[PDB]
Amino acid sequence: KVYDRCELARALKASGMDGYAGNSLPNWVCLSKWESSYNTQATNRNTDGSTDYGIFQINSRYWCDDGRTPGAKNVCGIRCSQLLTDDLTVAIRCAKRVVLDPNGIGAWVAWRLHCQNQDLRSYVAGCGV
Ligand SMILES: CC(=O)N[C@H]1[C@H](O[C@H]2C[C@@H](C(=O)NCCS(=O)(=O)O)N[C@@H]2CO)O[C@H](CO)[C@@H](OS(=O)(=O)O)[C@@H]1O
Image (cartoon, rainbow, N blue to C red; front, side, top):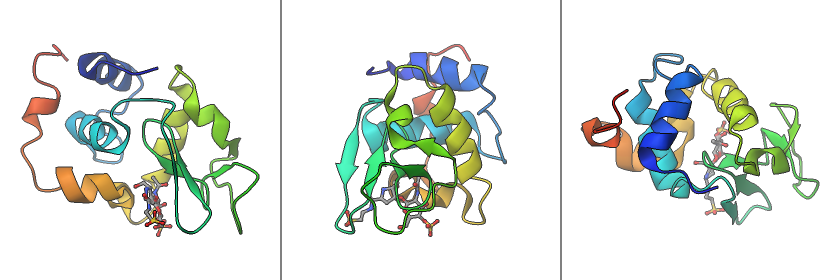
């Protein structure tokens, strides 16, 4: 599904992402925007054999199993295909596990590049959340 920015802002706020491990909502909307353009079916293969999956572009080397990644760990305990559904439940549960690591939200390249140190007001503007 391709989410509308406010539509996504409301689903994330409903699922407890606002303030999760100290990451305010706008951080989460900004990274989804730059990482997948809000598309849950986004896939991106990497030079190394892994693939990025979903709205948060979660990587198959460490978090999910796609059956074709060399030395994969599957920390979230899921098939990567579950990260591609219109229903964000599993993606959110795994994004939540990813930010508990020491690198926090800096695990996301697109957050580091387009959101870190920015004015993210605009990503939740007009959502009434
Ligand atoms: C969310 C998540 O899975 N984050 C992980 C991040 O995943 C990236 C790769 C990038 C990708 O686009 N890489 C480009 C490489 S290539 O295409 O040039 O091959 N798109 C994904 C999201 O930003 O990869 C790591 C290792 O570099 C991990 O850090 S870590 O140190 O925990 O493991 C983080 O776990």
